[PDB]
Amino acid sequence: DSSRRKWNKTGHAVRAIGRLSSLENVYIKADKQKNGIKANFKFRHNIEDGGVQLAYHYQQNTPIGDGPVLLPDNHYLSTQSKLSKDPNEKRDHMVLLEFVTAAGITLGMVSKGEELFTGVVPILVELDGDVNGHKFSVSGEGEGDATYGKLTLKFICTTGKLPVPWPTLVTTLVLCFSRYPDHMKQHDFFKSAMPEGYIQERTIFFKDDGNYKTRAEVKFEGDTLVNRIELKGIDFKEDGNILGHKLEYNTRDQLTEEQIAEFKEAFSLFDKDGDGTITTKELGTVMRSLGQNPTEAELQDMINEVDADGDGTIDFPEFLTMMARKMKYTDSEEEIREAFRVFDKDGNGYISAAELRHVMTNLGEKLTDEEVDEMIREADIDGDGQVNYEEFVQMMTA
Ligand SMILES: [Ca+2]
Ligand SMILES: [Ca+2]
Ligand SMILES: [Ca+2]
Ligand SMILES: [Ca+2]
Ligand SMILES: [Ca+2]
Ligand SMILES: [Ca+2]
Ligand SMILES: [Ca+2]
Ligand SMILES: [Ca+2]
Image 1 (cartoon, rainbow, N blue to C red):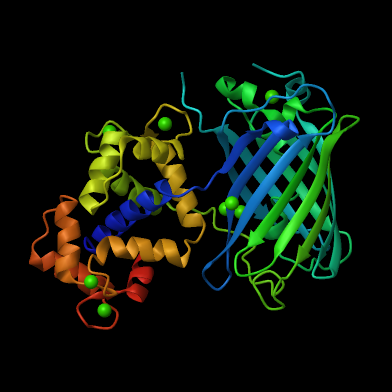
Image 2 (image 1 turned 30 degrees about the vertical axis):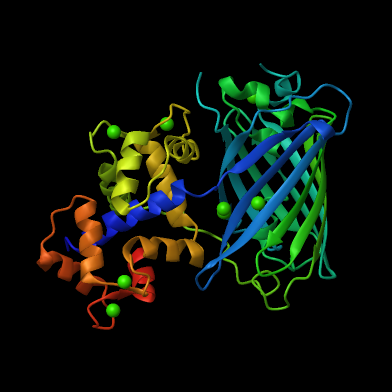
């Protein structure tokens, strides 16, 4: 009904502000001392029975050769991964489709190495791992098309059963296939190092669990881009999310026309002039009405995090993409409590009629005592005439 609808709209607006206030990309910076780069990012692994397992990545890349390389200005990669199974494959395996694009530098050149990536390039991946003494090997093959930032790879566990979930190896298992836009070609360290290649090293901290340490060599061997990796994992819990295999494999890419309609309702709460784009002025208006008070610089940074075309506004399509990702990957307890606190103004753990009234009428919706109570009632599982945390979580989940 049109009170379930008022939750969705208001809920989606609050989750849009949570996304814009988070750091979900691959952040790249120059490392002049090593003639390379550093990167850091957070990867979200959905836990099968509900919840999210966070993996915090720190990364270093250094050229294998002494040729000149491109040291970038600060930017990010935005990524999109889809995992599948080959229905005719009997071995323990993963099929990976990946798109990666560079952005984060607003609107206002090309290495010799970039010429090696103008068409489709065959890829080979080899990994040797040891997690808590559980050894394994992975072999992969496929191709990369950097013109579109596109990877297709199939991986086999050559040692039998993979002792960790496949999703935990995705980031370890060729950022030289990223699409850099024309205005960012001078910031592409990865292709610039080719064909001699680069060393990629990481430490990956699985929160409340162990860590991976990785070292990889990425270079051309003949016409093939090869990724050779060693992985060491330590201090994992015997029945944690990783060694207990509790992580989801296939995350939902299935996004209904009903869900898109819900996102467009939320969009139009921000896009108050109906021109199909959200400006810093429009984002700030909504945040102030929810009781936050961002500076111009914060608003610019929030938009920059999802601003695919670098024009300084969140276009409708950029808004749909950001919302699709936000529904695909589970929020942490901390992010859900932060959304809850937008409503629970007094912090007593209960969203009251007065509290939800105060939110709704500050967001500019004219709702009288009646439909407020209709909204409370829609979410009120236990009859107390208020919305508690668990009731909030249920309202917010698709
Ligand atoms: Ca992720
Ligand atoms: Ca990090
Ligand atoms: Ca994924
Ligand atoms: Ca290219
Ligand atoms: Ca607008
Ligand atoms: Ca834009
Ligand atoms: Ca309260
Ligand atoms: Ca209740």
